[PDB]
Length: 56
Length: 56
Length: 56
Length: 56
Image (cartoon, rainbow over all chains, first blue to last red; front, side):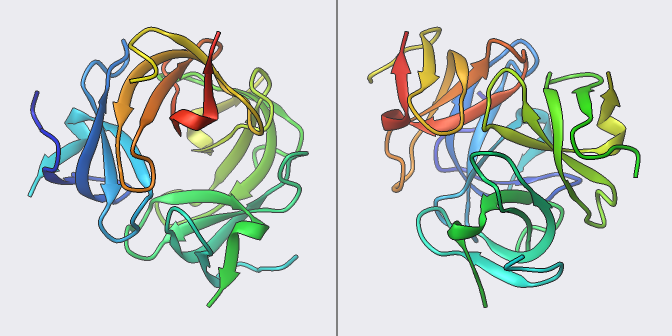
């Protein structure tokens, strides 16, 4: 696992998102995915493949 | 229409979101809905029923 | 506008989605975007750039 | 944990969604949340609080 719970991450490119890792998912299309709760918008969560994200 | 393009709005309660109205949708479940581009996270857009939102 | 309200469309590639155009959005990152209500999952709506979608 | 990986679940009410549990998230607003990959739309994943979902 590239990231763990509570890591602060951001989207590398395109649509912006930044905040803490709050969860995990895996599908065939996205075998390593993460749920990220926005630091700016508490309670709002988006999910992204690991390649979309970087730790800060 | 309660809101128009470019209005600054926020979620009234629960998961937070704030930024500008960038679009519209309508379904039977949500006959008056809005797309809101985050002011904190440019490019990221979420969609909400009108009752969830308030103009600021 | 490539599509209009009620057109039946699907995602061209990656994550699947199919149903009817129910709305529109525009941002700098996505200057021509569409809200698509799933035909399989009524009430659930996802939003996509026009290039992601094709009419069927 | 109410559900486990691979359980087939659906939304109880409102916007429809159905498919398999593919992940988990937790936030203060949603201390027990699940990612559900659509069975109708492979690759598409939505996330919901546990109270929104039921196993089938």
